[PDB]
Image (cartoon, rainbow, N blue to C red):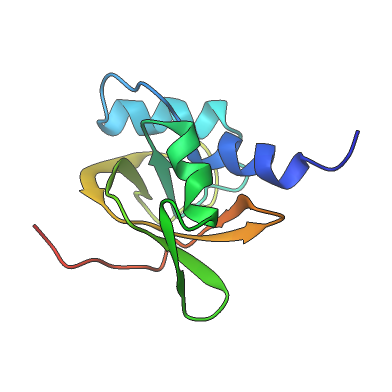
Amino acid sequence: AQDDYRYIHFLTQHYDAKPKGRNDEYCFNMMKNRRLTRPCKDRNTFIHGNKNDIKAICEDRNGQPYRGDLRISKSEFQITICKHKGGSSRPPCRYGATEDSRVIVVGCENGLPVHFDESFITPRH
């Protein structure tokens, strides 16, 4: 097929439409399901909600240029941040979850989001 991989890969590592727990157990299962445990990833953010509005950050409908090559969202998104506990690089990879709603920063390629900026911090609520 025509490379849609980076976009699908972004969705696999960062998207979960309708989550139910958004707690520590949620992160443990999700990091395992999405294959981010070998080695344990230190931090990973899952975005929830409408997929179309995430893709829309790559265009002017829901995004603005940020730091030249990135895009910052116009609207807030419900997100769950999973942060690794302990000093081991091996499973079981335990995580602490943080629920939040904020604007996010992503990198796009061909109008599709392909990178999530985990380093971005926001004007708090």
